[PDB]
Image (tube, coloured by chain):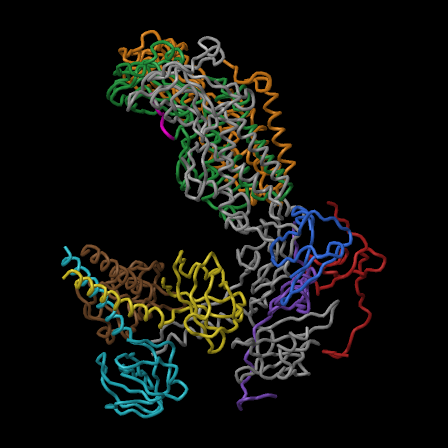
Chain colours: A cyan, B brown, C yellow, D purple, E red, G blue, H green, I orange
Amino acid sequence: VQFANNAASRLVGPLAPSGTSLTVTPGDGALFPTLGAGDWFMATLIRSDGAREIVKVTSRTVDAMSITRAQEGSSALSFNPNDRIEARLTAGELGDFRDGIASAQSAASAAQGTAD
Amino acid sequence: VQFANNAASRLVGPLAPSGTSLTVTPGDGALFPTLGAGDWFMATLIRSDGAREIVKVTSRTVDAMSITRAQEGSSALSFNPNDRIEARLTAGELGDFRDGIASAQSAASAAQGTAD
Amino acid sequence: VQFANNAASRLVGPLAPSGTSLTVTPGDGALFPTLGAGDWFMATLIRSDGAREIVKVTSRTVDAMSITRAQEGSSALSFNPNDRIEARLTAGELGDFRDGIASAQSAASAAQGTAD
Amino acid sequence: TTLKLTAYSGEVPRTLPRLLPDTASQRALNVRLDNGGLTPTRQPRFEANISVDNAKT
Amino acid sequence: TTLKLTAYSGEVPRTLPRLLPDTASQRALNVRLDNGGLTPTRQPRFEANISVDNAKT
Amino acid sequence: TRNDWMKTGPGNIVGGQFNGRYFASYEYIEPSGAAFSGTLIFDTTGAAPFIIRSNHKADAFFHELQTGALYFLVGKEIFEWDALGQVNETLSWRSKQFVLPMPTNFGAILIEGSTAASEEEQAAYDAERQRIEVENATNFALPNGDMMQRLPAEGFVSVSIYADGKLVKTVSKMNRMARLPSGFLARIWEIEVNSNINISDIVLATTGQELRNV
Amino acid sequence: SVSIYADGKLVKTVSKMNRMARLPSGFLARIWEIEVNSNINISDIVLATTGQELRNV
Amino acid sequence: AFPASVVLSRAATLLQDEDHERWTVDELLEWLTDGTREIVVRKPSAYMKTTTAALVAGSKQALPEDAIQLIDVPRNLKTDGSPGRAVTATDRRLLDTENPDWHSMKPAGQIRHYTYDSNVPTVFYTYPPAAAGVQVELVCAWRHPALTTQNDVVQMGAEFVSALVSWCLYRASSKDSEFANGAVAAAHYSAFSDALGAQATGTPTTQAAAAAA
Amino acid sequence: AFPASVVLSRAATLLQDEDHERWTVDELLEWLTDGTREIVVRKPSAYMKTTTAALVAGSKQALPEDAIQLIDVPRNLKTDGSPGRAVTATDRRLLDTENPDWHSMKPAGQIRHYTYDSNVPTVFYTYPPAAAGVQVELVCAWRHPALTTQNDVVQMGAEFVSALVSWCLYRASSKDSEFANGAVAAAHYSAFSDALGAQATGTPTTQAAAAAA
Amino acid sequence: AFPASVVLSRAATLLQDEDHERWTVDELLEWLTDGTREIVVRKPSAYMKTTTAALVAGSKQALPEDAIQLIDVPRNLKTDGSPGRAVTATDRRLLDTENPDWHSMKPAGQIRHYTYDSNVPTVFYTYPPAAAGVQVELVCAWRHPALTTQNDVVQMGAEFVSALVSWCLYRASSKDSEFANGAVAAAHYSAFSDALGAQATGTPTTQAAAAAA
């Protein structure tokens, strides 16, 4: 799960509530991480006003952004052609981190038990 | 240690420098993580002006949560009936993560040594 | 890699792009983590305007911190004696954590493999 | 072996750093040298904003 | 460690107080420095009165 | 030298005048992709001419002749130069490389001067505090807003001493003697002064008793 | 590369920088001259018969 | 029985370094412990305690490792609390000339005489040979172990504390020896030597060395 | 019986610092206590307090920890207020040679002799071994504990106020600052030594040293 | 039993070079070992090692090569652990005059006398000639071999750390560089000599020289 650093993109192409992809600005496309097959980063879509939704980036091609909806459970909404793609959702990432550290500790304990 | 997501509320009932419980706005109480026995999230109180104090939420019931002060070492402060409770602190949780990772490789190496 | 909390400081000394060390305001010096031998923390140097550079502090004494430049890929740029050093850059430590989780899991799996 | 710094002067980069005058110094940045000390410069104030981009005059 | 004040001179405020000349001094107020001493100024005397208020010339 | 002027770049020097001083703004790219931007103001008045450096790049300058204050354009905005009513900016001043005939270490620092007491700097600081409080209030009401609520400013003195090209100490005590570190012996010493307030003078000695002498 | 001419004869070529170097010994001359060859800039060269004299200046 | 904290405060008040930046607490503590060892050497009367020391089987004995010199061996401690017999010094050479195999003599429940030579500090012989680790109180020139922490306590007399202050002044002011060619350091050394010289109470350092028993 | 306040006033008068802003009052109190210790050492007659002390059962005894050296043991205090028997000094080595098990001898209600060696200040032996903590008057060179505050009193005589002033001046002007002077410090140390030298009343210091009974 | 690390830390603190850049750690180690040797020579009581050494058959014997001078030969060690007989010094010239073929007689299982001459340090004669390599305790002024690494331990007493520091300062400050000072070196040599002079415990150096038995 790759991560991004200080990348805010204007969502130039209007995105339907059931949308397979979105388009970032040409300048900000390279600002986001490179990604690859099987590697992804989550992004928070901030609409005008307080509306915020969280998505999953399967991959990027140049300035075109492949997207999937409703990862944390945020409801799908229609998107105007002026929006923000920035920030990293702490809930999913730190939850995965806490689960992974505990899983590693449990696996090490099981390995110790099997060795004994 | 659960994590919070996009949660920000006002401390409506004035908080003493020595406080046991906090009261958020009625609407936003559900947005904070529900938690359970022995399970907590860290919540930051950014009061008026630059002063901020960190606290640990042992548990939350309905809209009011029992609170514990002075976790990272921030001085206990009095807070006015208007406040902000939000954010996730880097130092404590991520320090826990770095300690857990090192514990994981240490336990794995110990397991391998016992196997040998 | 030690982590900082709520530490924003002005760079009182003009930091050349090829600069070994930098000095924050006297009051904010202790606000940075004390660090230790073999220990570093991420520091983002946000100058005037949007330009920014990221480095790690190898060691600090009193008010002055030793630095290692252009480590996370940011180009070396000049710095005004009115700057901001604060926050923590997402990419590096989180890549390290996602790699450490995988390393711990793989080492544990090899541990059961040797045990069997 | 005392060295005393008083009556400060500005930067003269056409000189070896060692061979500078006794009260001349490098990188006189954001300093106004009038009284003989390190009087700091004040901060700029945003008086007005220009309309058209890439203004050269 | 004697400090002797003789042949007084006037005020130069474009100089750090410690870096003033040996006989230059601050706040030379109501002093006429002609012979080299503190000759006091005389008090003004009221010669005549003006007719119309707020005279600028 | 010719080298320094050529590297500065005379092709794109933006010029300006303030109090009989030529304000030159230079923005040139050093090889290997390093950029230096700053203002080089020239004053020939005095015993000998010298350069006072500044770190405010300007796209264009305008010297309003009627009221002698420079107006320089940076970021599509008109900024006055050291105009009245603003808090003092951080000052950089790195001393001449002092090659002592005998390698020694210094054990006395006297940073004389006075705190802000002219009350116009105090008024400017109060205005800055009001601006900070206003921005804190307006960011405090955001529907919320993480971080922000920037810290107010402060008046400080920060003198850094370079032993032989290495920073050994940063001293902040003023009007009272301070101490460097020990265990290091160097002969090419230099002093850098960073502050928001003015400093009268700095004197160094290996011992306080020698500091008594001068 | 600093070459030292004792009395018209090259006695030594010293290449160490920023640290004390030593000439040869057993030759006594009174008309000394210094030759400096380098692709880089050099601040200064100072000569003394002893290191302790080099301490003096 | 003063702690090191006082002495560090004194030395940090003489030298205008109260927050300990030129002279850190660790090196000042080091100078304190070195001065304690030196002052015990100069005047043994400063720091004497009686220590219960068991003796390995055989005539040959070794005093506790961190002791400069034993002055007296007054009392031979009997099993558990009983003070037991006392011991007087004697000369080894007479013990050697006659009964030359006095080391091979049957070990005794309690030693009767001990032989000590100032030349050989660490070794003292016991007559008769000791048996089964009999313990004896030893009056020995113990050396102060170290001063690792500020709060650590120095078991020395409370005027040798000022002597340590002067010695630490010596060891700190020799660092900046450039000033006056170390004249101030020599002055502190002279003051320290005079301070121990005019110690009318303990062993007189002014008089003949080791003259006092 | 003078308080420390007067001596602090003197020291603030000599050094041209009456406000105590540079030489802090804590520092001057420290110099006062160091001076009290130093004069007590140089001239033991300065501060000798007769203290009644219980004696642990047995021949071995320990001087009170806040005492440099015991000079005399005049009276063996009988139970409650009765002064009791007197005690006279003897030789420890002959107490060892004859009756070698003198430590094991039955304890006595009142001790009869005491042996003290200058080399070991903290240990003095009693004859017979003490019983049930019998108390005896001890005349010893007591050390002034400390001077915490200005109003703290000094148990020494008002005679040595000049010596205390000179010692405080010596240890204060020896500071490494512009405001302190060095030749002044040396002259003040010499003045302190001379002032103690001309003390014709107490224990002599110049002519006879450590020979006072 | 102090390691060389502490003394190198001192010498790095005295000379204003804590990083050991100009004075390398090997160089300071070499000065430490030179100081140990010099202190052993000046005051033999500093380092005297009781060494059991086999004796070549015959009257002539050689002192262990790592020994300055043998001071006593207390015990003639019997086979395995038994201490055996004692040995007392005699006169070689009278051993020559009477029984001139005293080298040629039957060897003895245990030597009975030894003759040592100061003028010849490496040779000591035994009477009767030793047989089958009988070992004897030798008390000699051992020379500390070397200080290869910083953590290497110095076997001398911890009290001579001040003398070792003074010697290291004297030798390092005698370097012909800007960073070394000469008058400082002379004062440090004087300080080392004085520090060894006031060693009231060990062998006297100022008053009596080479007269210690």
Where, by quadrant of the figure, is residue A7 drawn? Answer: bottom left
- The reply to whether residue H157 is in sight is no
Taking the spot 30% from the left edge, 58% from the top edge, the residue there is B18
Total marks in image: 0
The span shown in magenta is H60-65
I17 shown above or below F124 = above
Where, by quadrant of the figure, is residue I137 drawn? Answer: top left
Q: Residue A71 at x, y = what percent?
A: 23, 80
> The C terminus of chain C appears in which quarter of the rendering?
bottom left
Q: Is residue H35 left or right of residue A61?
A: right
- The reply to whether residue G4 is in sight is yes
Residue at the far top in the pictured view: I98
As for residue H61 lying within the magenta part, the answer is yes
H198 shown above or below B90 = above
I188 shown above or below I16 = above
Q: Residue D54 at x, y = what percent?
A: 55, 89
Residue at the far right in the pictured view: E35
Q: Residue H116 at x, y = what percent?
A: 40, 18
